[PDB]
Image (spheres, rainbow, N blue to C red):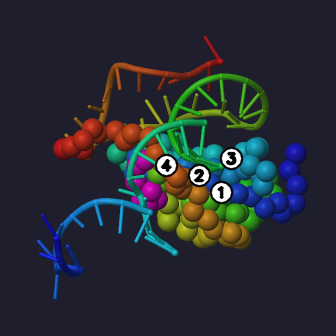
RNA sequence: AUUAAAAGGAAAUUGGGGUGACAGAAAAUAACGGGAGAGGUGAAAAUCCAU
């Protein structure tokens, strides 16, 4: 059920607590292989280390070239609804790992959601102490 | 029986001043992809997960 070189999309959602390496078809409805940081480490604190993000992104690519997807439209995103809109630590490691993995890199975009207007944020008035 | 006060009141623009009748985030629901973790912390656990 594989084909020749088919462009993919890599919605790499990496936050301060975890990382996600998700590749689908260009329609965005059928995923190809999705490996996250928590599937590559045993320590909870290391669910989003750059080594964890790069190792996961490494093994993700091998399946992509195995199935024929070689080029990826990267999409960068962090947990930025009402929280921090900056991509987490392992975001760059995951992208670079794919680049070292001999994958053509197409468009790169930031798909972190930006609320036109927002709900309440957790923490109350005085915030986190 | 004085005037016409850089006293006051009365008859071209400025105004997120007051009243009255477009946007996606967050979450839910529906359906599809995938099949093992996900949240969370300085570190963990109670928690959600093969329905």
Q: Marks 1 and 2, how far apart in space?
A: 7 Å
Q: Are marks 1 and 2 on the same chain?
A: yes
Question: Which badge, 4 or 1, comes first in the chain's sequence?
Answer: 1
Give the label on residue A10, or none: 1
Expressed as whole percent of the image width and height from the top left, the position of residue B7 reads: 17, 71
How far apart in space, not on screen, are marks 2 and 3 (Cα)? Answer: 8 Å
Tell me, yes or no, whether the highlighted magenta stretch contains residue A83.
yes
Q: Chain of mark 4?
A: A
N-terminal of the pair, mark 1 or mark 2, is: 1
Q: Is residue A54 above or below residue A96?
A: above
Residue sitting at 74 percent across and 58 percent down? Answer: A8
Determine which residue is flagged by label 2.
A21
* A5 horizontally vs A48: left or right: right
- For mark 3, give the secondary structure: strand
What residue did someone put label 4 on?
A117
Q: Quadrant of residue A11?
A: bottom right
Q: Which residues are magenta?
A: A82-90
Tag 2 secondary structure: strand
Chain letter of the residue beneath label 3 in the structure image: A
CA neighbours of label 1 inside 10 A, class few (<14), some (14 to 19), many (20+): many
């Amino acid at each position: 059920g594989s084909t020749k070189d088919a462009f993919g999309v890599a919605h790499i959602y990496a936050t301060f607590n975890d990382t996600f390496v998700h590749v689908t078809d260009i329609s965005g409805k059928e995923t190809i292989i999705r490996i996250t940081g928590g599937m590559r480490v045993k320590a909870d604190r290391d669910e989003s280390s750059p080594y964890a993000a790069m190792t996961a992104a490494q093994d993700v690519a091998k399946r992509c070239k195995d199935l024929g997807v070689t080029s990826l439209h990267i999409k960068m995103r962090g947990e930025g609804g009402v929280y921090s809109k900056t991509p987490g630590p392992g975001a760059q490691a995951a992208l670079r790992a794919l680049a070292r993995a001999n994958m053509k890199i197409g468009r790169i975009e930031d798909v972190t959601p930006i609320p036109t207007d927002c709900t309440k944020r957790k923490g109350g008035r005085r915030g986190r102490r």
